[PDB]
Image: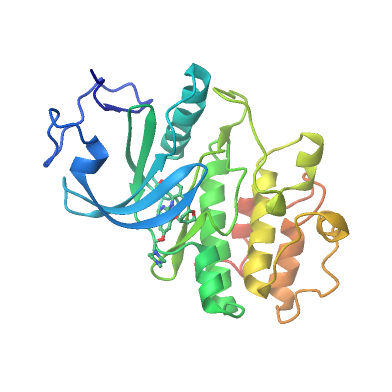
Length: 287
Ligand SMILES: CN1CCN(CCOc2cc(OC3CCOCC3)c3c(Nc4c(Cl)ccc5c4OCO5)ncnc3c2)CC1
């Protein structure tokens, strides 16, 4: 016998039965199989898979990430479901990827969010060369709007990277993938973890983290996409970047204005590093 799929939420609303057009609770196929139409595979890793699908419910498009294998235990389950809790903590914001719903069936977690344009990373590798700076500024601003929304709620993304920023057509963009998001001070179902080492803030090397870590992460995110360079995973080059230095190559082809802003974001000392609000308050970054 099989447990039925059940909604995963932390809002405290009723415990409720997942139902959908095309979904027969009798039939053995999963809720995701019956209630959706897999259109393409957006990605795959050890996290599982992301699918571009069309809901049989409202007929519209979404992205659904399903975990790869059943939960290994209670603790393993709690930490996976926490991603939903995080995403729900973000709430409604135009610069943040919106969560539609989530559910679990057979130890597998399904996360259904809005379908976005390609990630900044995908858009960058497709563009071939450096992005126009007018584009880059728009990317920098929308992510800062997203960060300020997170940071004003005591939330830290902790894994801001080009692959987490999605081109909102056009040419806006949204911050998503809240798997590592922590609410400062109430942590946590699971312990906090650093993000991608390529974009990691220097203070995390000694176990320190605040909202400032995101600002640094966004800095190297923008540096990567605007120079079309590739960031080191280690060594002196990596360590130079965390010491206020710039790659001796230097960001050539970048203006003074954009360079001076990145310096504010790439500041080694967290307490000196600019905040998102202060950055957005500059004038070179208004609407
Ligand atoms: C060849 N083209 C096909 C269409 N495509 C537009 C849509 O591109 C995406 C890709 C996503 O994820 C990929 C980005 C890097 O991470 C892995 C694959 C999207 C995405 N991912 C997602 C992530 Cl990262 C985290 C949690 C999720 C997610 O969906 C549901 O819950 N989410 C929303 N839209 C995506 C669109 C261009 C290229």
